[PDB]
Image (tube, grey):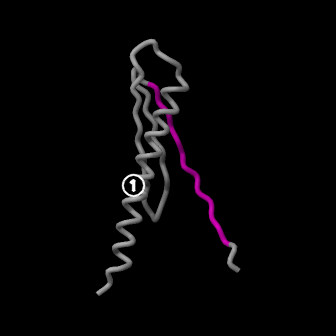
Amino acid sequence: SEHVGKTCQIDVLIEEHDERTRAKARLSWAGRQMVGVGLARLDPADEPVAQIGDELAIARALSDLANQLFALTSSDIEASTHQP
């Protein structure tokens, strides 16, 4: 006591359309499926690569999910107090 931690996995999918690569980052949290969605871009042409589009999409997906988790934190904080 007190050493207990826990383990999640975030499942990332990257789909390249084109132009036009999209990432989805899915987290199961507090009994809800949370999905961050990110989109690139690039550019049209030429073209790049590939890794650039993927990593930018993932970055935007994770930001989205982070922002959703920040919104959940605030909501929960506000729920915990007030309690009148």
Q: Position of residue 76 (x, y in %)?
A: 38, 70
- Kindly state the secondary structure of the residue where label 1 is placed: helix
Q: Amino acid at mark 1?
A: Gln
Judged from this view, the residue extending furthest toward the left is 84
Q: Is 11 included in the stretch rendered in magenta?
A: yes
Q: Position of residue 62 (x, y in %)?
A: 47, 45
The residue depicted at 53 percent of the width and 19 percent of the height is: 49
The residue depicted at 41 percent of the width and 65 percent of the height is: 73
Residue 84 appears in which quarter of the rendering? bottom left
The residue depicted at 43 percent of the width and 58 percent of the height is: 69
Q: Position of residue 64 (x, y in %)?
A: 40, 47
Q: Position of residue 59 (x, y in %)?
A: 48, 39
On screen, residue 8 versus residue 83, left or right, reads right
The residue depicted at 41 percent of the width and 38 percent of the height is: 38
Q: State which quarter of the image contains the N terminus.
A: bottom right
Provide the residue designation for mark 1: 68
Q: What are the residue bounds of the magenta stretch?
A: 4-16
Judged from this view, the residue extending furthest toward the top is 46
Above or below, 72 against 19 in this view is below
Q: Is 34 included in the stretch rendered in magenta?
A: no
Count of marks, rendered view: 1
Above or below, 73 against 34 in this view is below
Judged from this view, the residue extending furthest toward the bottom is 84
Give the class, few, some or many, for how many residues have Cα within 10 Å of label 1's Cα (few <14, many ≥20).
Answer: some
Above or below, 26 against 53 in this view is below
